[PDB]
């Protein structure tokens, strides 16, 4: 079930809900943290982007990041992670898709996202201890999908809404 859409915002997301984010333009898509040892950032890159540095607002300040997208047809979401409050975001995972949809979810002890190349992208996860101060921000409209209906989230990620 597609709950939404919702306008951009920041909150402590309840566990077991995919945030399916649907941006229209390249740029920062989302960020999230448990405030202790994980800071996540997702950016969207348009097709045919040669190695370059782009500036994004992350964790409250401007940050320069290396990006590229070798595809002529798919857009590319890139997940960056830093593991300390004053560390350095580094590229961790990518999703290549012509549909410009990405998703993430919090569960007990994990954060999930989709990775690979549509239409055969699949879920990946990272050990993350959730807390009462955890928070996530979406810069684009998004939907919520219950974890019980993960198959439908996968359907949308790979094949479009």
Image (cartoon, rainbow, N blue to C red):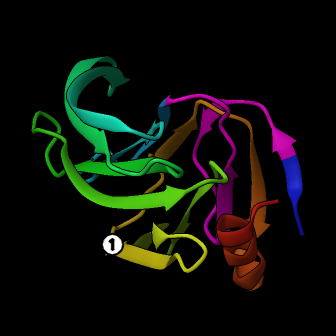
Observer able to see residue 109: no
Q: What stretch is highlighted in magenta?
A: 5-26
In the displayed structure image, the side of residue 54 where residue 109 appears, left or right: right
**What residue is drawn where x is 64% and y is 52%?**
101
Residue 125, by quadrant, is: bottom left
From the top left corner, tell me how far across and down residue 87 is, in percent: 9, 39
From the top left corner, tell me how far across and down residue 106 is, in percent: 52, 66
User: Furthest-left residue in view?
Assistant: 87
> Which of the pair 58/46 is nearer the observer?
46
- Whether 153 is drawn above or below 44: the answer is below
Q: Is residue 128 magenta?
A: no
User: Furthest-front residue in view?
Assistant: 72
**What residue is drawn where x is 81% and y is 39%?**
6
Q: In which quarter of the image is the N terminus?
A: bottom right
Please name the residue that numbered disc 1 is placed on: 126
From the top left corner, tell me how far across and down residue 84 is, in percent: 13, 45
Q: How crowded is mark 1: few (under 14 residues within 10 Å), some or many (20 or more)?
A: few
**What residue is drawn where x is 62% and y is 48%?**
100
- Whether 157 is drawn above or below 36: the answer is below
Residue 154, by quadrant, is: bottom right
In the displayed structure image, the side of residue 111 where residue 64 appears, left or right: left
User: Furthest-top residue in view?
Assistant: 62
């Amino acid at each position: 079930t597609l709950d939404g859409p919702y306008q951009p915002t920041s909150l402590n997301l309840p566990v077991d809900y995919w945030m399916l984010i649907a941006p229209t333009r390249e740029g920062k898509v989302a960020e999230g943290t448990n405030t202790t040892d994980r800071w996540f950032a997702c950016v969207l890159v348009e097709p045919n982007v040669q190695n370059t540095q782009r500036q994004y607002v992350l964790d409250g300040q401007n940050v320069q990041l290396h990006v590229s997208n070798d595809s002529s047809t798919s857009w590319k979401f890139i997940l960056f992670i830093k593991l300390t409050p004053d560390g350095t975001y580094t590229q961790y995972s990518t999703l290549s898709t012509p549909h410009k949809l990405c998703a993430w979810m919090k569960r007990d002890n994990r954060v999930y996202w989709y990775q690979g190349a549509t239409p055969n992208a699949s879920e990946s996860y990272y050990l993350t201890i959730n807390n009462d101060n955890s928070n996530v921000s979406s810069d684009a409209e998004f939907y919520l999908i219950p974890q019980s209906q993960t198959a439908m989230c996968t359907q949308y990620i790979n094949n479009g809404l």
